[PDB]
Image: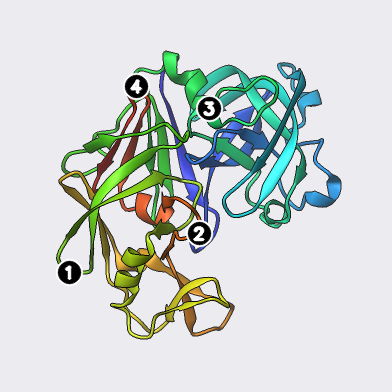
Amino acid sequence: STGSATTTPIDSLDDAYITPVQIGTPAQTLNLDFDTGSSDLWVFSSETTASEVDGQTIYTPSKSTTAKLLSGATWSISYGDGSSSSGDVYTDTVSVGGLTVTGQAVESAKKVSSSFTEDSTIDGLLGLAFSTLNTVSPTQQKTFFDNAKASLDSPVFTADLGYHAPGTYNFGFIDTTAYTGSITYTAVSTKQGFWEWTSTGYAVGSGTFKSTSIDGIADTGTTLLYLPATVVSAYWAQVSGAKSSSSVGGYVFPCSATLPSFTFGVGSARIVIPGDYIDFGPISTGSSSCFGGIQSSAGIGINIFGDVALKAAFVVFNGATTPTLGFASK
């Protein structure tokens, strides 16, 4: 089997992407944030504190003939940005782009933090990291991908995120029309539960390539590119007037600037992020100070190849017995 679904930016900055997901019988379609940096499929639901719902579409298990309470199971998660959610668990039928899993753990939110409430476009998350990070207790549950894997033509999914445009998540096949040149594959460590890999270096604009190992995770659920302070300083030094602002919470630059591209290494291959991808616009409405899309990972504890980086590439998440990551230009 295979699946194929379109993923759409939630706003004009590509802050996140939503993908329609069918849950239950008859189908209830929710727009979920596919997140390769976590491993819980959770939804706004009929159980969510009413004051914490503001425009989201909710899953109502009582209206699904295939929903079953997973008796005793609870979940609670906190994300890198400080947001959180928690609740109880149902199993139900879940389909993504024509690909169906029966008995998928659907984690029903009783509580969500402000950040989730305030984002009316995101109805929940669909985690695609390794199932070892799943927070369901006392019986840990599998991701959608893990459940689907054995039925897939190939044990892979691909992320093809658009810049200010829709893209595609495919399951079970590699669309050879979706990228240019060849795909370069690189080793993955699953030791922390993430799609963790090592970039071979970077360049800033038309500058010479710096060979240096940068360990990081491929994370579709993170907006920006977070790299070591040395790298990020070298990038922003090439932008007149750019500075790290503690008041704003990272690097800002004059909105009148033209940003240089940023290149990262995948083995001997190179992925180029156009400068425009690194512009996240005024810090506040009407400001001439703009927020940068490359930020320091210092104090996160890990480097994160988020959407800014991933949307410049066609990315293969290979879940074979020995997982790997593939990157192609497009």
Residue identified by numbered label 2: 299
Tell which of 129 and 61 is nearer to you: 129
Horizontal and vertical percent for residue 299? Answer: 50, 59
Q: Which is nearer the N-term, disc 3 or disc 4?
A: 3
Tell which of 327 and 65 is nearer to you: 327
Q: Do the residues labelled 1 and 2 touch (CB within 8 Å)?
A: no
Residue type at numbered disc 1: Ser
Residue identified by numbered label 3: 132
3D distance between C-alphas at marks 1 and 2: 29 Å
Horizontal and vertical percent for residue 63? Answer: 78, 25
Looking at the rendered structure, the secondary structure element under dot 2 is: loop
Asked if residue 57 can be seen in this view, the reply is no
Looking at the rendered structure, the secondary structure element under dot 1 is: loop
Horizontal side of 155 relative to 44 (left or right) equals left
Q: Residues within 10 Å of mark 1 (few under 14, many from 20)?
A: few
Q: Which residue lies furthest to the right in this view?
A: 50
Determine whether 28 is above or below 260 in the image: above
Residue identified by numbered label 1: 206
3D distance between C-alphas at marks 3 and 1: 41 Å
Residue type at numbered disc 2: Gly
Looking at the rendered structure, the secondary structure element under dot 3 is: helix
Which of the numbered marks, if any, corresponds to residue 320?
A: 4
**In front: label 3 or label 4:** 3
3D distance between C-alphas at marks 2 and 3: 24 Å
Q: In which quarter of the image is residue 188?
A: top left
Residue type at numbered disc 3: Thr
